[PDB]
Structure formats: C-alpha cells, structure tokens
Amino acid sequence: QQINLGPSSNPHAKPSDFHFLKVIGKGSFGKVLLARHKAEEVFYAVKVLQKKAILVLLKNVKHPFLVGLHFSFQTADKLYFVLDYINGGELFYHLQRERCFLEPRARFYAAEIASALGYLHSLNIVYRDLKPENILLDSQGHIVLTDFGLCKENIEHNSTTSTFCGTPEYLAPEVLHKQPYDRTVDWWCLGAVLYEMLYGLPPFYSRNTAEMYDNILNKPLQLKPNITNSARHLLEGLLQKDRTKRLGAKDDFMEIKSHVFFSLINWDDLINKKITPPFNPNVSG
Ligand SMILES: O=C(O)c1ccc(-c2c[nH]c3ncc(-c4ccccc4)cc23)cc1
C-alpha cells in the first residue's frame, strides 16, 4: 500500500519526530501545519494529505522561487511533506496594507514569478492554478511559490464555489471551458497577478461569482489610465481571452522575458538573487 514518493522519500521519518503547533492553511486539497522538529529544533511547514484522496504522485522541482522540499514520508493513512517555513508574509497581505504597488516593485515580483513559470515550462511542467494564496515572500523579500511538485491531476480537489465572495483565483477563459491545462494558462495567471498588484483588485472582478465568470469570458479588458504604456501593453498581451493570441503562445517565457515592461530586468541577476528586493519584511528567520 506504500505510495511511491520519489527521491525526497524518508524511510526513517515518523510524525512523532514533530511538534505540531497550529494549522497554517489549506490549498485545493489536504492541510498545511506549522511544525517544530522535536530533535532538530527548527520550524517547518508540513503538508499532510490523506491517502483516500489519490484517485508518480510527487515530482519536486528545485528553483530559487519555488518553496524547498526537505523530505517526505508516509503512515498507513497519511502522506507528509516537509517544506521551508516561509515567514515574510503572503504577497497579497503586503498588497492589502498598501492598496496597490508602484510599477518598479510590481515588476520585480512579476519577474520572479515569470522566471519560475518559464523554468517549469522548460521541464514540461504547468502550474495550472497560480493563486494569491500560493504567493509568499521570504525573510529577505524574495518571491516563494508554494507548489512543490504534487500531481494535482491525480489528487481529488475540494472545490465548490460560493455565489458571492469566492476563493481568490484567476480562472482563464479556457479553464472555465474545461479545456486541457497548458502553459498559456500560467501566463493568464501572471497577467492577473500583475493586474491586481497595480489596481488592487483582480481583473474582471465582481462581488457576484457568476458575474465575474461572465466578465472573464465576455467583457473586454478594462485598463484604467494610471499605468505606463508598457504595463498596458503587457497586460493586453497576457490577458488575451484567446490563448492562441496570448503573450507566450509561440515562444513561451521568451515573449515575457523580452517584453518592454521587463527591459530594466537583468534575468541572470534576478534568478540568482543578486538584485536587492524593493521591500524588506519586518522579520528574520
Ligand atoms: O499546497 C498547499 O496548499 C500549500 C503548500 C505549502 C504551503 C507552505 C509551505 N511553506 C509555507 N510557509 C508558510 C506558509 C504560510 C504561513 C502563514 C500564512 C500563510 C501561509 C505556508 C507555507 C502552503 C500551502
């Protein structure tokens, strides 16, 4: 009954190695807990998924902007995954406190997310459902995305939706049409994150969920005149409804990488964290 977890697997690790403090959060499946390793005396985030949710399950990818996986293990009923505890706060918590970001700062976060997505696509992996709840900052103020390689397609999601005030997600037109997830959905999500970073609300927003779905599919893009033309151009490109016309359809990350909005970004410097972040979270750990 032992599930194959991959190279990260730990035959020696048991739950009794961990002090479990509180519930950190919940994605689309399972739960995440704050845990202090009894012996090691350090803090981790342990995702715990129940075996009665699986209908190669884990394919971890290392990258400077993807949350690090330390090891994984299992019991009779549950699977456990030990991750870095990221204490710089959720990106959108900082956005909340500020209403919106200036473009240079928004650009920096968008660039880090873009590089991780572009890296993932090169290894033939698609993010699928990038959401604000997935976007954290580390102690230094660099972006950390919470996906660590779990196969979403093989795990049963818990996803009903409310008519008013749903879970914050960026559903692309093609996702609503329930068409295969490909690399161009990730670019729609990038554009939506960038849109929200600039305007303080997701694009096509409505209090009513159905209205929002309606707006995503049928309402033309609304770009108020408070951003530079390069920002406008990028958002017009990334938030195309037709994914065959969308920025990234023909050359993927190279189209975003070479876009005028990111002209001031040295992509080698960024990926290697040589650019001092535009904001320092008021903590260290
Ligand atoms: O798949 C998922 O739902 C998932 C997988 C990993 C995480 C996660 C890994 N490390 C973390 N560190 C901190 C926090 C955190 C701390 C305070 C407030 C909110 C989040 C979350 C994580 C989260 C979700």
Image (cartoon, rainbow, N blue to C red):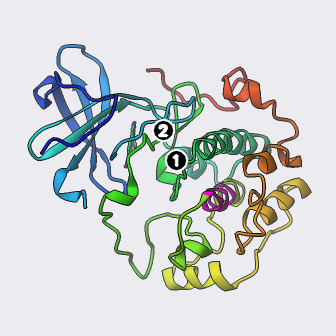
- The percent position of residue 252, horizontal first and vertical second, equals 73, 52
The label on residue 89 is 2
Ligand 1: give its quadrant: top left
Q: Is mark 2 within 8 Å of ligand 1?
A: yes
- Give the side of residue 75 with respect to residue 263, left or right: left
Q: Which residues are magenta?
A: 183-191
The residue at the point 33 percent across, 63 percent down is: 157
- Give the side of residue 151 with respect to residue 280, left or right: left
Q: Is 156 located above or below residue 141 in the figure?
A: below
- Give the side of residue 183 with respect to residue 35, left or right: right
Element type at marker 2? loop
Element type at marker 1? helix
Using the rendered view, name the quadrant where residue 12 is placed. top left
Mark 2: amino acid: Gly
Magenta residues, dominant SS class = helix
**Is residue 64 magenta-colored?**
no
Q: Nearer the viewer, residue 29 or 279?
A: 29
Residue bearing mark 1: 93
Q: Is mark 1 within 8 Å of ligand 1?
A: no
Cα–Cα span, label 2 and label 1: 7 Å
Q: Nearer the viewer, residue 161 or 6?
A: 6
Q: Is 173 located above or below residue 136 in the figure?
A: below
Marks 2 and 1 in Cβ contact (< 8 Å): yes
Mark 1: amino acid: Tyr
Q: Which image quarter holds the N terminus?
A: top left
